[PDB]
Amino acid sequence: VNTALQEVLKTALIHDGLARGIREAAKALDKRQAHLCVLASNCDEPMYVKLVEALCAEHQINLIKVDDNKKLGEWVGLCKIDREGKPRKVVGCSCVVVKDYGKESQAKDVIEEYFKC
Amino acid sequence: KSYTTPKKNKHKRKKVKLAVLKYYKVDENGKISRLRRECPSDECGAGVFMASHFDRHYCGKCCLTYCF
Image (cartoon, rainbow over all chains, first blue to last red; front, side, top):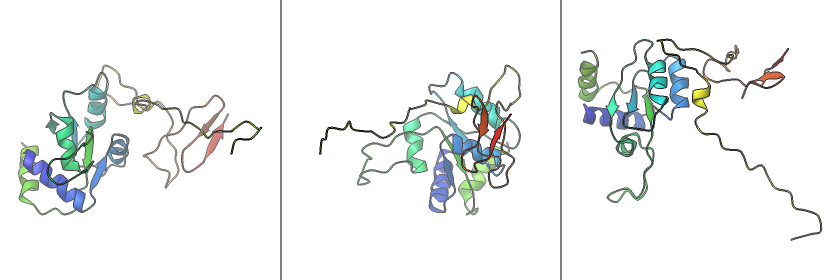
């Protein structure tokens, strides 16, 4: 679930397993070692949603629906300003590509058994 | 110091908004297409894209120039 997603995103942030942005996500997808991608819904996407569907609909690529763009930017560590309490301003992202290297967590197995269902 | 000669300025780079959707083109069916050509170099591999100029074809970091 979502706490499993934020825990595996934090583990990738610590062990350098993140590919943020959209063109870096496309390069990691065409390099054919991408495993999981996340697409944010309720966004300004007249063409982008079926564009990323065309990229992610080939084989072995799953999908995770997250509503708010600002909330998902916390888990990826896109910005961290004035960490004493709430952030001052964190800009939101669109897509994230993980590189699971520290592959020992119950969050990973619960998100994978969500994936294979 | 202001002199009699006019002052030169650096490149104020033109800003492009969402150019990645001009790399691929999507149809109404279920297929993915490549609008431009992919560089066949080894380290300059399958991630980067390559230009479409009026007379020549040039990549980004590996610098392989092709023309007709």
